[PDB]
């Protein structure tokens, strides 16, 4: 139940939500017993875990006449949400709106099923320090360390290929085309040039789209490894 | 650690005489923790990914150099220096299956301080300069 929802939320990847000329980063895990949601805007993080009874109550208050079991409602909500989260530009009708309070955040979702209306609301409170930590702070550090290790491995491979280049140059041969010649690789100079030139544009996170577009498999792998131990 | 507060007691010998101090810390607001940990780390991850892409491009250029040297009829004195063609997907798969567990081990913060502190400072400086 609650533990399963927490594990599912932990193991899910981030998605980009475009709503009312604004952007959010969302993770959603919906099962027949309930659902869990984590929202962020690079400034604050909100979490909401809801069970079956609250689902039925809220579905009744919002949809005053929608007499359906909680399982069907949750299944329809998942079917509506997952296509958007997995990929944008999907041909689905799902409008999102955001309202703010002192601490609460209201995420309103409106859609249509077989041409009839369908409303839902998420009342996301501020997330606890443990959740935000375990979800963002540690996985990001793991990704950074893994990327540094990958960079070191690539540097070693480049050094080996440089040794091959040196051997072949000593052999005395010449290239048929001289334009392919490449200067020897030096890690310090490469790092300095990168920092001087490309870092300002590469470190720009913007509204979070680069994060979801680029780093979503390494994040999942790091989270899965963390779950094991 | 009492309630939500933290008392950090520091004792020192100021010219051989006692020196006591007590930092009283309260849980930081979401904005401070965010701007101090979350966004900078994302910047570092993106920068490292860009570095990996650049290194892959350099490896591809070196592979082209190897291919042209082979086509030129040149023979290397030592056959042991031969290196296999670099493929990004295969390298990523091998890394993720073999070395990810050890690389991603955060531990207790020591590797983060030891390895990634120039990138963190650069990202923070860029953020400050932007606004």
Image: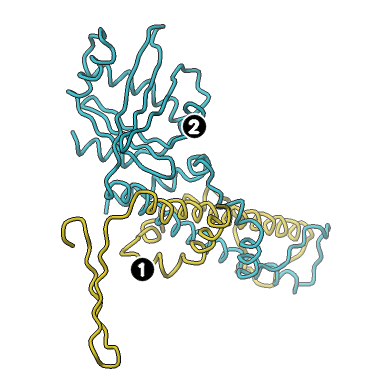
Chain colours: A cyan, B yellow
The quarter of the rendered structure image containing the C terminus of chain A is bottom left
Question: Marks 1 and 2: CB-CB under 8 Å?
Answer: no
**Discs 1, 2: same chain:** no
- Report in which chain the residue with disc 2 lies: A
> Which residue appears at 51% of the width and 40% of the height?
A207
Residue hosting label 1: B110
- Report in which chain the residue with disc 1 lies: B
What is the x, y in percent for residue B45?
49, 53
Of B114 and A102, nearer the camera is: A102
> Which residue appears at 47% of the width and 66% of the height?
B117
Q: Is residue A47 above or below residue A108?
A: below
Relative placement, left or right, of A31 versus A145 is left
Residue hosting label 2: A22
Residue A185 quadrant: bottom right
Of A36 and A181, nearer the camera is: A36
Gap in angstroms between the C-alphas marked 1 and 2: 38 Å
Relative placement, left or right, of A156 versus A116 is right
**Closer mark to the observer between disc 1 and disc 2:** 2
> Which residue appears at 31% of the width and 32% of the height?
A29
Q: Is residue A64 above or below residue A94?
A: above
> Which residue appears at 32% of the width and 51% of the height?
A133
Relative placement, left or right, of A167 versus B124 is right
What is the x, y in percent for residue A206?
54, 44
The 10 Å Cα crowd at callout 1, few under 14, some 14 to 19, many 20 or more, is few
Residue B6's disc number: none
């Amino acid at each position: 139940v609650m533990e399963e929802l927490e594990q599912g939320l932990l193991m899910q990847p981030w998605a980009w939500l475009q709503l009312a000329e604004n952007s959010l980063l969302a993770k959603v895990f919906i099962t027949k017993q309930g659902y869990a949601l984590l929202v962020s805007d690079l400034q604050q993080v909100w979490h909401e875990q809801v069970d079956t009874s609250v689902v039925s109550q809220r579905a009744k208050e919002l949809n005053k006449r929608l007499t359906a079991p909680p399982a069907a409602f949750l299944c329809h909500l998942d079917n509506l949400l997952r296509p958007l989260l997995k990929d944008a530009a999907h041909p689905s009708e799902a409008t999102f709106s955001c309202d703010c309070v002192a601490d609460a955040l209201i995420l309103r979702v409106r859609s249509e099923l077989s041409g009839l209306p369908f409303y839902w609301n998420f009342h996301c409170m501020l997330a606890s320090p443990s959740l935000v930590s375990q979800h963002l702070i540690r996985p990001l550090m793991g990704m950074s360390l893994a990327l540094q290790c990958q960079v070191r491995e690539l540097a070693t491979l480049l050094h080996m290929k440089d040794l091959e280049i040196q051997d072949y140059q000593e052999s005395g041969a010449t290239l048929i085309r001289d334009r392919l010649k490449t200067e020897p690789f030096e890690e310090n100079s490469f790092l300095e040039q990168f920092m001087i030139e490309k870092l300002p544009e590469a470190c720009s996170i913007g509204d979070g789209k680069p994060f979801v577009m680029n780093l979503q498999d390494l994040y999942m792998a790091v989270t899965t490894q963390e779950v094991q131990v | 650690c009492v309630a939500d507060a933290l008392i950090l007691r520091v004792r020192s010998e100021l010219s051989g005489l006692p020196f006591y101090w007590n930092f009283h810390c309260m849980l930081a607001s979401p904005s401070l923790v965010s701007q101090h940990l979350i966004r900078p780390l994302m910047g570092m991850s993106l920068a490292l990914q860009c570095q990996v892409r650049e290194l892959a491009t350099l490896l591809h250029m070196k592979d082209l150099e190897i291919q042209d040297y082979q086509e030129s009829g040149a023979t290397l004195i030592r056959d042991r220096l031969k290196t296999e063609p670099f493929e990004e997907n295969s390298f990523l798969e091998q890394f993720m299956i073999e070395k990810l567990p050890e690389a991603c081990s955060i531990g207790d913060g020591k590797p983060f301080v030891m390895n990634l502190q120039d990138l963190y400072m650069a990202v923070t400086t860029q953020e400050v300069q932007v606004g």
